[PDB]
Image 1 (spheres, each protein chain N blue to C red):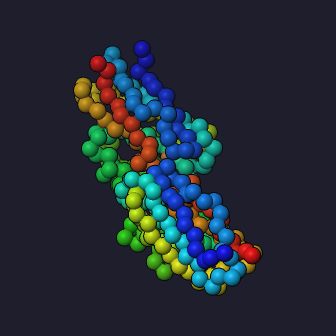
Image 2: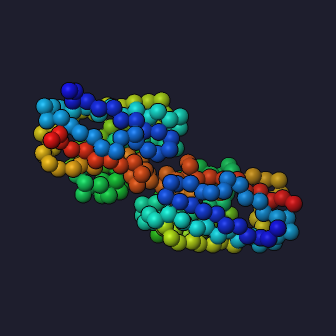
Image 3: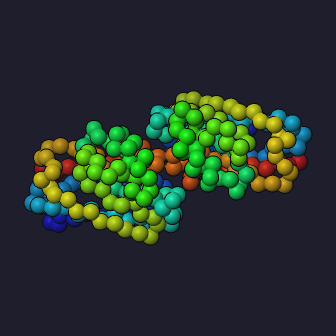
Amino acid sequence: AQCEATIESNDAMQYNLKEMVVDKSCKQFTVHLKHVGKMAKVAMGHNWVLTKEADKQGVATDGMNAGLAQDYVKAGDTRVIAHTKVIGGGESDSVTFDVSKLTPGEAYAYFCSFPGHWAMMKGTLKLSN
Amino acid sequence: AQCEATIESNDAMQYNLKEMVVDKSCKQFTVHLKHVGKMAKVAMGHNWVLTKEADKQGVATDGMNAGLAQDYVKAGDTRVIAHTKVIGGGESDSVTFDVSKLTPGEAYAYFCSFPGHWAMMKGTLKLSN
Ligand SMILES: [Cu+2]
Ligand SMILES: [Cu+2]
């Protein structure tokens, strides 16, 4: 139902959710990302980035090149639907986005853009009723 | 006996050895790194890099900026005692170095300098006793 979801990231380099569903009644959707580990952001920071599935690699690449001060996301990347900041163990961050950016029936990829994390930290997001 | 060791790396971002000992009877030592997972190097490439414990973070930071083609290790890095190339699943690489670069009693760190892997893929190397 409600237009929110909580996802956990840890020191093992995993998310705890592999799929997220945004209910069709939602106009706004909020993702709460938590880092439940204890490692520093420079060593094991995590974020949550949303792109079309297609755009995964590219956004990941450019993000890595953007640096930590940019939360490992190329500024103004248009391929990026929404993203959180990079957070370390014990922290959390939230992002709220307009559902209208998503198109029904389409596949969206969410992943962590911190260097090298995208390969193990990825999931699918979809709009459904 | 031998002045050689095999160390495995996998898709879970781990090495299978946490510590390595080089026998004092050795003049040279060879490390054979194997990537026994099935991920490709662009997503989960691994290397093996040896430095003094203290040069870890810096070598890693800078190897990261050298890129894949440079095996994620800055060329001519004086802090690097030895390193293999970056390999992907189903591949192996070997590196041999002089034992005399080592100092009896000292703990050296070995780790994977591929983006983001250092936090998890790290161990200790030293001389026999
Ligand atoms: Cu991450
Ligand atoms: Cu690695």
